[PDB]
Image (cartoon, coloured by chain):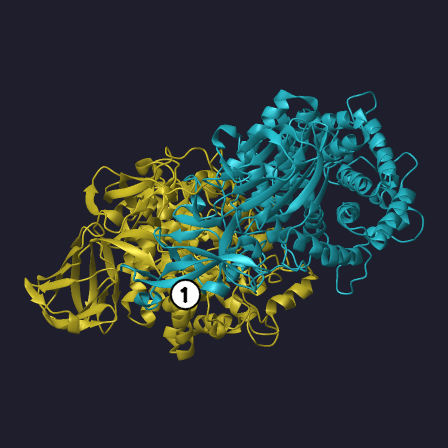
Chain colours: A yellow, B cyan
Amino acid sequence: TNVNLKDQFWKRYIDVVRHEVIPYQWEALNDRIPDAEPSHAIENFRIAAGESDGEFYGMVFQDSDVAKWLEAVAYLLETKRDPELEKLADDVIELLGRAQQPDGYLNTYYTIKEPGKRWMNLRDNHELYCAGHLIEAAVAYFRATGKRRFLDIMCKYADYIGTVFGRGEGQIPGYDGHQEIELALLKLYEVTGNENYLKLSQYFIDQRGQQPYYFDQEKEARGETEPFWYDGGYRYHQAHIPVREQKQAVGHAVRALYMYTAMAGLAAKMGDESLKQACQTLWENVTKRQMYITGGVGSSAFGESFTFDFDLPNDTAYAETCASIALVFWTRRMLELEMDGKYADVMERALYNGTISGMDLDGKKFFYVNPLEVWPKACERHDKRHVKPVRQKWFSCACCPPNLARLIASIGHYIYLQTSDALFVHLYVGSDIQTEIDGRSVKIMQETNYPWDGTVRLTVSPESAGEFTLGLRIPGWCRGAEVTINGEKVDIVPLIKKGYAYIRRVWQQGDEVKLYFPMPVERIKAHPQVRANAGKVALQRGPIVYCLEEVDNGPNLANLFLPRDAKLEAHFEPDLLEGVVVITGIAERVDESAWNDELYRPIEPRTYKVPFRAIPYYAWCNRGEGEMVVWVNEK
Amino acid sequence: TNVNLKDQFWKRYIDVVRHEVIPYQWEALNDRIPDAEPSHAIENFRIAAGESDGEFYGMVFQDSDVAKWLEAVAYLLETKRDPELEKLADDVIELLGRAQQPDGYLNTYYTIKEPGKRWMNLRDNHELYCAGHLIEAAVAYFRATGKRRFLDIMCKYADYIGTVFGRGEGQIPGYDGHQEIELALLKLYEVTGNENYLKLSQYFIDQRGQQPYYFDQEKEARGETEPFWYDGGYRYHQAHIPVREQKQAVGHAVRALYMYTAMAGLAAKMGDESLKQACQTLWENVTKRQMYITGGVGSSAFGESFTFDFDLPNDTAYAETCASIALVFWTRRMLELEMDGKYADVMERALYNGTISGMDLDGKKFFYVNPLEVWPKACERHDKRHVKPVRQKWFSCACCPPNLARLIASIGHYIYLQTSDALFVHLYVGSDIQTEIDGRSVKIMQETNYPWDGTVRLTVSPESAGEFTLGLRIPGWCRGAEVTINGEKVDIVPLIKKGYAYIRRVWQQGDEVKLYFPMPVERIKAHPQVRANAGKVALQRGPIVYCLEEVDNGPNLANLFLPRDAKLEAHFEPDLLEGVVVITGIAERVDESAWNDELYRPIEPRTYKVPFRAIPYYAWCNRGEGEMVVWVNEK
């Protein structure tokens, strides 16, 4: 399976990651950006390798920043070799190899700052989290370059971790306050075939939330008495009860979704039905009760967390970039657990909305928080101070960048899934794939202007003719999908199972499948239990959720009312925001001129008509500070 | 001027304060309530008088709780002598006299806990605030009983304070972090004629906010380096700039309104036009941009503070009971500065909505915070944790009670104002007053079922016939007010000036003025800049703002839509909530069904008709926990 991107939309983002984002982060990691908060991330490994002097600096999880940058670089190298970039990575890798302790432990903070204090604060100090991120980078770097050095280093650490943690004699019955090692270990298993890694992942998941609480035991041993800052206590870490008894998403959103992603991978690999069902129950809870229309998750700044069903406020949303990325990871494992278009529908929602919303179109600035409603003046409220009205650079928790980079750079890995049963098309993205079906070589090409248009042309070319199944997602946002094969209509209705059309036939060289997904402008309504959206409507076209910005429509977007009957139109604007479809129509505003400086009046408001224009949510805040809303008042 | 209450509405509240609220607090102040947080408020004075041993206990402003209870008791004694209650007060008073230092200083914390450390932390430790509250209680107790002892004690302290603070040689150019002393000093001046008190008040106000900052000077002297916890710094205390440059309300709402109250009193008494204009500018800002329809003020829990113009969220409101009480105090001084009905309109709005909303109808439980929208489950959000979904008892900052008690108990003082050129009727409350106009003895009787009905009968009986002016407020909520004198209709339009009808004529014994204020059900709309209320409407009848509760309408009050043409009806329910007018009609809900557990859908919502019933805002949460909204979605 090699996949080449051949589109406009994602190719532009990859180019931005390659030329702007990854190089800038490299400078930051090496403290060569004069105005920046220093990182010391590379320096810490130098000191640890005994090649430099100085004090540890930065956050306890600083090592993971280096990991994430390496992981993204790995993916970049799969789609364009660059010997200089590869050399930078190789040198960092050898440095990691020299900072690594003889027993396999690799952690700058506990090598330089608190030697000998390792494994005494898993609740807070992210040791396994950093190890997990480094494992992911090493796996990725191996798959991209064939070079095993980083993989070898990380297997030594993974083996050491296996000796330290478990239910055995002299082992710690522990796990990390921030999940990540569990999903990373699955990847390491997939590339090595070493079953210890699969079992260790299972151990960490099965042990979480067991009584007596591991976190209480280590806390006691540190002599710590203070109550945990987060009111829900261990719900923050989803360590309140065992994972199979968790029926609602709670706590910190990234933590949760990384945990779920591991649970879904383990359910698939182990055939564990109880875990599969837990995943499905959690999936339904997150995606049908605690998810924003943008694919954002996390409704409370305090703990960057889930709250509860249907509590999805737009102005105080957290919807962290990293959580939406984590949702994408989760969906991919859910798809391996069960082929249901609803998983890919979510993946696509996050991909085209609440992930990429996290960056400026040119990749120079980022959001941590992705709100669905902005009144900039109000961002001075204490309960809105997490909401930044414009994107910026970050430091300390500068994850928005190497985090988005690793997803965007690997976008090719999410388009297709080769199974022995079928070749599945999840995303409609100009691309090609060279794969093997029933031991035979098959080339598949997608040509499409998606997401701006719903027409997709798939050319299927097997090396020699042969029978196999092509599984095509029918997007849940779409009504009335149509399919033709070599110009002849095919009734897909009997071929559809759980949002995928299964097309099984003998394929010949140059066979052509045409897909047509109508993209009308839709008015989306939220379930009536979503109190924040009572009387409000969102615009969506294809997979893209739209928003209104002040720059196009004036201030006071709360005072814009979209009548039900207003006739909406869409058209392409090549020179706007890198080339986007915009949506236009006629709305109504209440007349303030008719107001008289009173605050409250018993009068019937007078309304006048205004043109409006809406643009894609992901593209907001590229034309200066201003109001923005997704959910607009109706009628 | 003697005023007797003869109504049902306020009389019931006064009885509750007299029989439940004041006696319960007396027990709490003496630590005789088993399952309460101890107060030690009386005990601290015992220790300070050398009549008991032990450590200081409680908040630095604990002394003010005793003061507020005494002040209320004073007002209770004006409307019904009670030798036992008077005895309790007299004993407390003699105790205060024995706790007082030889120089006049009276403060338990700086007598027992930090002897000699007085006046070193005016920013935080409330010394002048407690002195102020004690002064108010003494003034009130003198007016009520003729007993001067408490007054004599407090004059000694006030004189001492006058030697300590000022611009003179050896004086501290300081002022309290919590305003109060300034308005208290005006009251002491009014009852003693001692001009020092008036000038001292003027000094505290003129000094506030002058550079170099007093609070920085004392902070430095304490060796304190920590930044102030509130992000706006000295805006919290309204000490950021001089008062006559403050054009917006900012900071902590009670602090601000106590300051404004002093400013308005001084502008009147000193004839200071610059201060008058400053008060007017602030008045307009508060009441036309930063006030809730309930008379609540304070839109941010953090700092219990004002935010900025038109930021009035209903679900995260703070609208502290004490701030609404403070607004009432402010309006009374504004009325002395300028006879404008808009002042009394706000006074009335607070009195019948966001003050008495602070207690259960039987006076046993209280709110600190008065929200305008409640979803109880959501009160677990960190950004809503200040919102309690049911009333309770309080401890430490148990001000809601002795604070409401003092206002309710003194409600008679707010009904009329005698000036040398007119008798003004501000509030429509069954009552009578014996007063002197142009040296002539005049008796006036009001009979009315206000607020449930807008008909008022005033009987005017001068000792002998004579020409004078009666000023009658024409409520700003009203349209088509009518006035009839001895059965003949009078054209009031030419008699009205700034919301008061000036009726000047020769009055004879038994003259009858009938006022009729129509009370239709009104749909109130907020200025379009109020984002929170875009697309919403509030119901109001007479001075009373209405709300919907779950107990009458079912859950999910966000999913209730009030059509503009729905017919509304009002009628009296004698056995509901101590006897209230309710409002009824037909609203619409969106039908849950068409979602089928989806979260977001492109479907046209189906709506069905439901009955609704609205009750007075003040009377919400007397029938158990449940949803409540004031601002209802419109269709």
Q: Which residue is mark 1?
A: A261
Judge by depth and name the residue closer to the eye, B32 or A492.
Answer: B32
Residue B62, x across and y down, in percent: 78, 48
Question: Quarter holding the N terminus of chain A?
Answer: bottom left
Residue A449, x across and y down, in percent: 18, 50
Residue visible at 82% across and 56% down in the picture:
B30
Judge by depth and name the residue closer to the eye, A625 or A154.
Answer: A625
Indicate left or right for B145 with B257 as reference.
Answer: right
Indicate left or right for B577 with A27 as reference.
Answer: right
Judge by depth and name the residue closer to the eye, B34 or A59.
Answer: B34
Residue A344, x across and y down, in percent: 29, 63
The residue under label 1 is which amino acid type?
Thr
Secondary structure state at the residue bearing disc 1:
helix
Give the chain letter at badge 1.
Answer: A
Judge by depth and name the residue closer to the eye, B28 or A100.
Answer: B28
Number of residue marks: 1
Indicate left or right for B351 with A24 as reference.
Answer: right
Q: Is residue B229 visible?
A: no
Residue visible at 20% across and 39% down in the picture:
A574
Tell me the quarter of the picture where residue B416 sits: top right
Residue A105, x across and y down, in percent: 54, 60
Farthest residue toward the left?
A487
Q: Is residue A471 visible?
A: yes
Q: Residues within 10 Å of mark 1 (few under 14, many from 20)?
A: many
Q: Is residue B289 above or below residue B47?
A: above
Q: Is residue A602 above or below residue A520?
A: above
Q: Is residue A370 above or below residue B388?
A: above
